[PDB]
Amino acid sequence: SNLKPFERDISTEIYQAGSTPCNGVEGFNCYFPLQSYGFQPTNGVGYQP
Amino acid sequence: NCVADYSVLYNSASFSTFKCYGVSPTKLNDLCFTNVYADSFVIRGDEVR
Image (cartoon, rainbow over all chains, first blue to last red; front, side):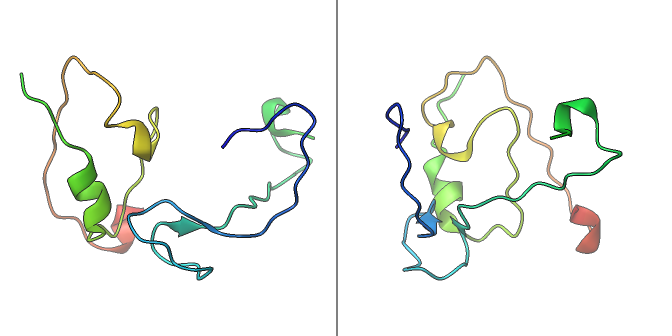
């Protein structure tokens, strides 16, 4: 669910987007919650830090 | 002129590629569209990228 204002809960539980939970195993329809971003000096302005 | 149930193919989990843009995967069932084009064919594996 979305955040309430000023909410910071650090979790690494992979969430199940499919019809069956994967129980913490990165598999089908169970993505990793944390996405990293490829900062580059050549990145576009919309993607620069 | 037909209502589409978007849960059958999303929960079949037989698809090796499922990339949706402009709409999220689990809000297809909520939305109401004017028309949808379906393009069916066979492409080699690494070409699907």
